[PDB]
Image 1: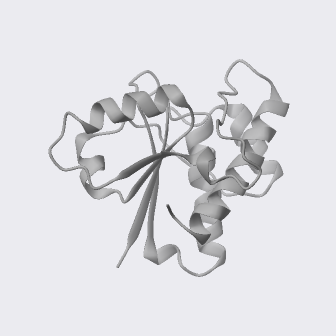
Image 2: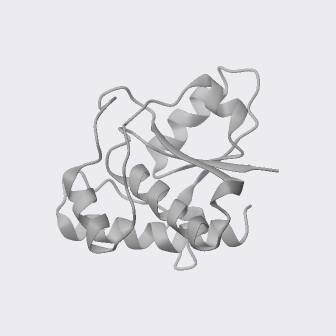
Length: 154
């Protein structure tokens, strides 16, 4: 059976596209990309159509992690079709729980991606107002959490 994960933050340009790209690389490298539906989306509509933040794209290039994405907003359907929706911070979590209670079919388990970190950093902080070093931190957290999630889901 295909498994599916949707990575979510506020605008779908900073953290969630990096998590998606990292997770795709992990499954592709283990020959199991065909078995996984992997995507990212926004809680808000501010950035719809936009490519990832240029600084996140630069971070990803340095790491040779493949990233190519068009921002989109989460839809009602996404709660029916995804097995996991993995978000970045408490505001995302609150909004997603709100949206999941306005639909009838919520298959998805909604969790903080950080809840998978062995190094126990629960929040993946918005790097929007930060600098290149903040994007790097985000990348490193995503690697740790995506590995652990792939190994064993809650």
